[PDB]
Image (cartoon, coloured by chain):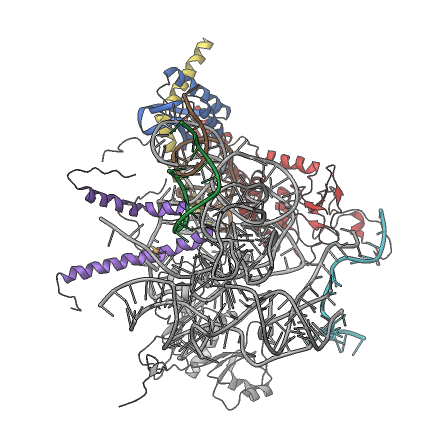
Chain colours: B yellow, C orange, D blue, E red, F purple, I brown, L green, M cyan
Amino acid sequence: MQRACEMVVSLLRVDALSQRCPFHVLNVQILDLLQREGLIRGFKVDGTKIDILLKHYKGAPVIRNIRVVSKPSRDIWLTPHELKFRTRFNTGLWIMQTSCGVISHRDCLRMGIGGKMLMAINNGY
Amino acid sequence: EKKVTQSLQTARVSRRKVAHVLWLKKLQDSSDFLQEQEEAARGVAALARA
Amino acid sequence: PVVFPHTRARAGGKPIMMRGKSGKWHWLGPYWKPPWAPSNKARWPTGPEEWAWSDPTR
Amino acid sequence: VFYETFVLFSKRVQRADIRQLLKQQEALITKHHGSMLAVRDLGWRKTAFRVIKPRQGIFWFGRLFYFSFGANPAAITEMSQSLQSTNGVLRHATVRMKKRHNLMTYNHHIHAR
Amino acid sequence: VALKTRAPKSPWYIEAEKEFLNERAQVPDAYIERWHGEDLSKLSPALRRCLHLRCASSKELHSWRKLQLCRLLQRRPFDTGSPAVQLACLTEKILNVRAHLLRHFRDQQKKKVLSIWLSRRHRVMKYLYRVDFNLYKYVCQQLRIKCVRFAIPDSRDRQRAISPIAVDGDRCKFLIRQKLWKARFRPRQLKQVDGKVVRFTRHPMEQPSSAWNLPKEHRPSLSRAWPYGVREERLKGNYVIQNPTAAGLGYCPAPLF
Amino acid sequence: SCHRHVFRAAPAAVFASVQRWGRRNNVHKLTLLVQTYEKPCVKRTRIAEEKAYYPRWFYLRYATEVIRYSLKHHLRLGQA
Amino acid sequence: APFPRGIVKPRSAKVRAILNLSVEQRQPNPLRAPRKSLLDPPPCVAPLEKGNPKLDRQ
RNA sequence: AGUCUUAAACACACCGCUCGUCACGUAACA
RNA sequence: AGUUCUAUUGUGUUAGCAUGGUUUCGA
RNA sequence: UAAUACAGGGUUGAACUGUGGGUUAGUUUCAAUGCCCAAGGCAGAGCACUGGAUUGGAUACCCAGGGAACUGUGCUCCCAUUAAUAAGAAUC
RNA sequence: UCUUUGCCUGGAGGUUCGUACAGUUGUAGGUAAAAGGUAUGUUAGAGACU
RNA sequence: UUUUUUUUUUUUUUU
RNA sequence: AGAUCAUCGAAUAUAACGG
RNA sequence: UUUUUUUUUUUUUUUUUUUUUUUUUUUUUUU
RNA sequence: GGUACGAAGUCGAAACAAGGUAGUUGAUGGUGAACCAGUGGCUGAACAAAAA
């Protein structure tokens, strides 16, 4: 779980093209969801470290703000009816860790199952 | 495969010990008093018995 | 095989020199390499000189 | 392990004394489970500065001697103290025998080339 | 007013201290650097004396002991990283430093190094206990080391916690435990035959009995101590002690030195 | 110790050589320090300060040499 | 070289410019700070001349 | 005498700034 | 990371020695 | 801080091992100077102390004498408290 | 970006094994600015030169 | 006379 | 019938059972 | 008080490692 | 004994900047008041300061 929070520092760079990241089982699954939304150009497992590319548009990067909700020292859980109040009138991306794999916040409400808020992408206050 | 490395280790140490014996042999040869005292010792041994 | 590096933390502490007019070391001496130092190849790119000895077996 | 000792005699030292001195030393060697290696001589040596030793006088030169031996490491202290009490010996030192650098196996082609 | 001074040394403490050094100075009839007779045959009789252990130094003498002990617990030739070999190697290193501290007492820098090795050896036993239980008991018997099991977390109380210093209780009889001197367990002042009054900061080191934390035969009964009686195994006197290195109530572990 | 012999040279010229000899060995600096007792704390800071000023002096001394050398020769280097 | 018996650990920029060899500002680390450029706004400082400001355009 | 460099607890800027013993008066922990 | 072996040692302890400022002596 | 004895740490080569760890009390060593006690002495230095200077009205600044303090297996950590103002992991 | 230990809340103040052990910042008579610092000016029996 | 101080004194040597 | 943070008064800690 | 000579006693940091040379590799927005 | 506030008199020139001939600090000694002498540590340290 500790290695998951170490990906925000590397992926949050302006003047860079590719950054390394420690190899982890959970980290690989997270990158898949981000690529679908069009946030990561691509990634490759280089053995002990994973090389992840950075996407840019008109100079500025596609990622501008990263918020870590879940931490190794504690665990944030929200009911299906409570996640909607938290996440409303926004374009942000919340990573939800449900029993049936990992999915975004939009899919969590559709199934109505209780997920787990891991991190936030392109989120304001 | 571990047993294969066991034979290699024995050969490696064997060569190292071989070079050590050569150094000690030099000392013996180079030593004069060692030989002189040794030589004398032997002579007396036979004279006493005879 | 895949193996990850180990923690750089080690036992002991940093070098300390005793105070007062009696100059003496407490734990470690000047010849102490920290665990976060760079590789020796980069620190001494010149390497042994032509007039250097090729056998340090003193 | 092996050991080396360099003893610098004086002008007032005859061949009689040298034999006696070495015989005494051998006693200690044997005591501690040891054996003598070899004994050699270096002849006379010129001194850079005058040597003023108390109750001995003043000397400008002496006879340099060298002898190798081997005994227990604890025998170095006993040997060192014996030399100092004995007359004639004005200066001495004990040097451990090394593998490569030695006066036995390495004595040729030093100054030449 | 009493003066704080060091306590006198007990008569038995001095006698045991000298005996320990005598054992460490013993020189058996053997050879160093694995100088088997095969190579020694090429040397002269005179020269062979020098190579004997009697003519060897402390470094060579200490190294020889490690080889003999390693072979006793050697799984395969040229293998020293196994926990069984490491357990014996560390034991010899601790005694080597302890003997040096007796002759040299002004070397305060090495005092901290000894603690590192003592703690390091303790962690080795914990790992070996969970991976192999049968082997953990066999190694203790050969080395006469107090076997201790790790099945429950250790309590925070010092009167019943573990003590890495007293691990080798069988081999060391003067580093088992001592008395408390913190607030109420302090010693009372006394007057020597000197026309003066002094006080000891530390209590005297008494000689403990041989039955320190050992099983004993119990008697069946029904009282406060045994609300449900006494088990059958307890009566025979064969139960296994989980923490044999416990100092017990009203006692403290011995100091590091 | 230093010894010099006068041979076909004026006393003033010879005396100028021995005077500079002490500067290399710091004869004057050591003579005055031993006269007065200096506290150990002062030497702790003085020894460190001398390790930053003296190195800087050597670099500036070389720069002055180029100015004098180039003045008598004119010319100037550029990004050619 | 001389054998120092200790070391100085200053904290103020006043004496730090004397004991240390130099106090020149090195290039900022790209991994912590951005690269400086001439396009940044200038500092807000008023013009002064011997204590008398000059804020006239003739 | 006019500038340059450095230091500063002052900027009604050295006729600056600031501390201590003793004398008198009003009070809370007595 | 740790154990063994090998090369390396102005790091801890250590009684006699050599040299030297000061001091002391005058067949 | 040349020689010698005991035992540590760091760099490189081979073998072995195959997750052994980060922080750390109801815990344990060491720790400049000063003071009590003790051991001490015949050198180089000096607090207190009548021993030769003060003032434009008061003094320890400048010489000299001077019985405390200066080597401890001890009692013992008050400080401007001993190699920066973080003990670890990730981005070069 | 993440794990764990320790510590502080403007400045400021206190009666006139038993004389031992343990333990301590806090219950006021009073106050509204203590203070880090970039720059300018001024002073300097503090360094240099027309 | 020597020593010392910005200057001076105290102190020490006696053909 | 099961589970079900304690807080203030500054603080001062090891106690009760059997040989 | 100066110079010279020949052996008493206490004490032990003057000489001997260095242009701080890794992507310079790190110290805190503003005046 | 010691401390707070208001007013304000006498006796002194300690801090500032090398004038008090550097100045705060740990433990002692001493002095009508600035505090002063010695040892340890620090800079929150002023002046001066290398070629053959």
Instruction: Name, please, the residue furthest toward the top.
Output: B50
Residue L11 vertical position relative to residue F41 in the rendered view, above or below: above
State the count of labels. 0
Answer with the quarter of the image where residue F66 lies. bottom left
Residue E63 placement (x, y as % from top left): 51, 39
For the C terminus of chain E, which image quadrant?
top right
Q: Residue at x 70, y 57 (%)?
A: E157
Residue E24 vertical position relative to residue E163 in the rendered view, above or below: above
Residue E88 placement (x, y as % from top left): 57, 45
Residue E26 vertical position relative to residue A76 in the rendered view, above or below: above
Judge by depth and name the residue closer to the eye, E108 or E18.
Answer: E108
**Image-based side of D41 in relation to E137, left or right:** left
Residue C43 placement (x, y as % from top left): 35, 56
Residue B29 placement (x, y as % from top left): 35, 26
Residue E238 vertical position relative to residue D91 in the rendered view, above or below: below
Judge by depth and name the residue closer to the eye, E198 or E134.
Answer: E198
**Image-based side of E219 in relation to E128, left or right:** right
Judge by depth and name the residue closer to the eye, A118 or D92.
Answer: D92
Instruction: Name, please, the residue furthest toward the right.
Output: E222
**Image-based side of M9 in relation to E66, left or right:** right
**Image-based side of E191 in relation to C35, left or right:** right
Q: Residue at x 36, y 55 (%)?
A: F51
Judge by depth and name the residue closer to the eye, D3 or A23.
Answer: D3
- The answer to whether any part of residue D34 appears in the image is yes
- The answer to whether any part of residue E88 appears in the image is no
